[PDB]
Image (tube, rainbow over all chains, first blue to last red; front, side, top):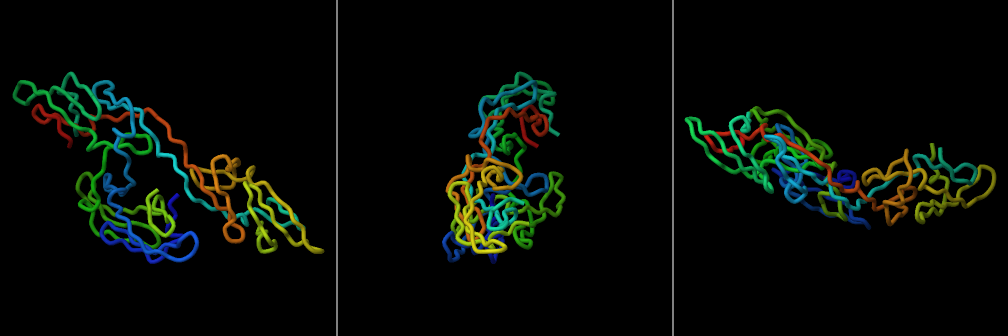
Length: 101
Length: 101
Length: 101
């Protein structure tokens, strides 16, 4: 999840904009930018990843008791993500034969 | 802070909107509304008090090493503290282009 | 620990199965295979050891370079979870009018 710095070089943050040179899936490199102002927020003096508008991602909003907002809210949306794992870590050649160690 | 419910009566929530009838300081009553969609948000299935735009409320934004966004941000109580966040969490390289996932 | 690659030739991933041709200690070569499904887990979109069953939630499995397993993996399933927040925390009655503070 994420993991851009592993495949990108020459990164800089100018104001609220991140710029980097990232590898392509089949070779070459591409310089590109992304404004982080729409995904990061200031919560109590601590930078954080911001959530969703709750009226689009929750159901049955209601008052509970005297002062409580209650809802059934949705978790992070499900998506497909590229990932990799080094098979050298635990797969071995043991007399011509592959096994786990 | 806050605690409207100690001086207000007949509260209701419809959508993102809170409506209540509150006591005026020097006697009498007033029904008013507030939109909770501008101050509350959904964080991975939990409702939380929204933070602030970090550009207009933080100072000295810089990349720290590989993938860290570093700055000093105004706390609730308006005093600056040093804060960092790892951009690798959610910024990915999608075929040469930088994208939030 | 492991490192089959630097001793094994012509490796391929079909589904969850690694098939390669490896050199014996005393002799020539042998082609064997190992099912990785029962040994690699998909944890929220990241391939990991110390678990099983990744193949049910990951697609387009390929060999990247000489020893890397590459895939497109499903992140945690989205679900509706009950949540509450206390409005008293930051909503006040300012002279009969609801305000955020």
